[PDB]
Length: 183
Image 1 (cartoon, rainbow, N blue to C red):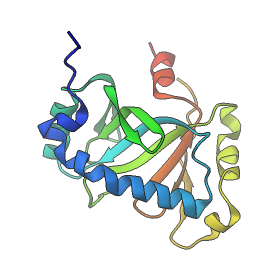
Image 2 (cartoon, helix red, strand yellow; image 1 turned 90 degrees about the vertical axis):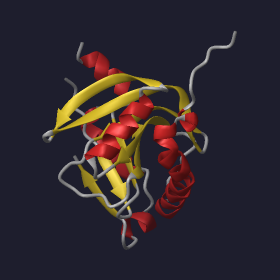
Image 3 (tube, rainbow, N blue to C red; image 1 turned 120 degrees about the vertical axis):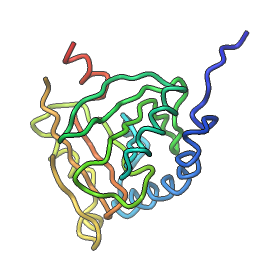
Image 4 (cartoon, rainbow, N blue to C red; image 1 turned 135 degrees about the horizontal axis):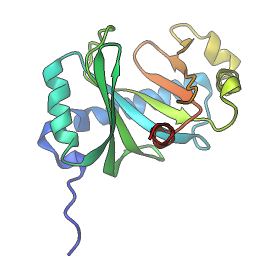
């Protein structure tokens, strides 16, 4: 018989983020359009959530443990960040995100509990990651108001472009590769 593997959209504990996805799809589509970023050729790595309540993080953890498996859990700035690999992906446009990042509440307070950013892997030399990512963004986009850009074992330089609430990041490695680098 076909394997019974709960899809993330079927889990009671994840109903809020399932309902929050359409909003995020629009957010990413719009941000990419303003930045003049061509999404089609870019390789998806993982999608990330943000919460401000510990209870919310715990609830989502219980939910992801019903539709995925833990890839890693690391202490980042005094709080845990879990990376889960799901049996079935979170569909975002043409992308199929199999890995979800679940960070506990940290220093910065994000008012919205739900989808917040995605990370793209740009193969090549880590030393030029920032420069290569910046080259993918149009001049008009970078100069647009409200839009900002910032920078952040294996060197994992991460270039992040944002509108204030929705963010797209680029880095040299995939999560599975980072996990492998430390075994």
